[PDB]
Amino acid sequence: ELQLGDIFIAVKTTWAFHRSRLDLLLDTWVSRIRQQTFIFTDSPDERLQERLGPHLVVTQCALSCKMAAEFDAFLVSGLRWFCHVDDDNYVNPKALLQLLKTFPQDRDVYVGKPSLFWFATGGAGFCINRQLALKMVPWASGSHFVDTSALIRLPDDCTVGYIIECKLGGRLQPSPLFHSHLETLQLLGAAQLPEQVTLSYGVFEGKLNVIKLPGPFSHEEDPSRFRSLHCLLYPDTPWCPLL
Ligand SMILES: [K+]
Image (cartoon, rainbow, N blue to C red; front, side, top):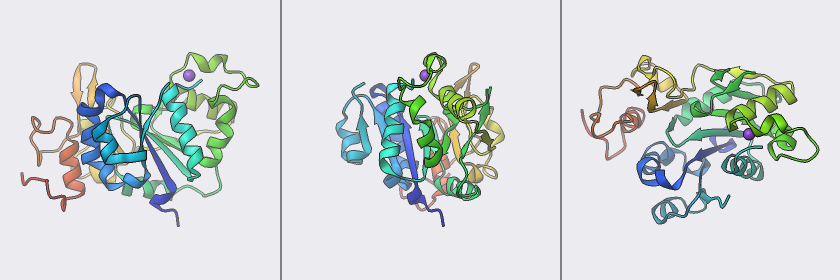
């Protein structure tokens, strides 16, 4: 009985990437799940403001100021599930809902792709339910009645895992379905690709790391492969080409 309406998807971006990254996401996966997706940035934008309205959150800035903004906005929302992704992630909402239905409904859950205390790599995307997120507030807000000395020199993703494992006694539940670009993405082809919850694109150890799809867009038209993935998943989309 969990539905898509129970999920708050937060995307982190910055002004310098509005044209280069954000427009691509708005054309592709954000167009299939706009009602649940909120874009956190640091300057206004006429084009994004047009397409998103209040779904464009312009911040004027323990956790970084944008991540604190995402947590605060999620809690205000009241929704059961929080999922964080970066501006170089692709989200499959159908695969996401199927995974989230798999957890017992009254247990704390933190799910993602593990990295070394264990933490979910932020560039792969990760999800937390409301009950666990509400328990994180004292640390996540940098409040004056908990110890955050350890929190101040950790990145956002690490900080999240530390709070959950080290302060709350919880545990990361690993899933093979979340993917960063710190991963050899070429093992994921047309056959595996539809079962995945997130994909990524980017440079790591000197290699442009992308999923393996022959088309329907060329690498020159679609270097991230996100347009091609989108067309595999949603072939009814009018702007999808043949190849
Ligand atoms: K921190």
